[PDB]
Length: 54
Length: 54
Image (spheres, each protein chain N blue to C red):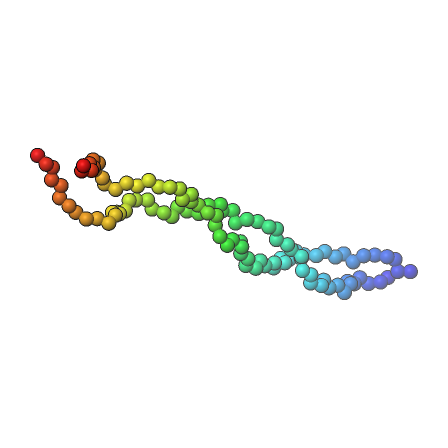
């Protein structure tokens, strides 16, 4: 009878060569930035008085 | 006695089944864009002469 035995085997390392495709963040628009509140402006003025003739 | 020998062995290729987890681009705000200064504006404008009665 041929007695049982096992071949002495060992594997060596290798690099999978994995690769990554190109993707996108998917961002389509930034958030808003602005209130648009009422803004005060006055032209160069001088104050007078007005009298109606009677 | 049986003379030594080596088994006929071959390793088949296999994909590693790698998956890429989710991530964010990491940025939160853009850069300052506007430039603040004053510009000139005047309403519809006509000149007169002012005489004070003395």
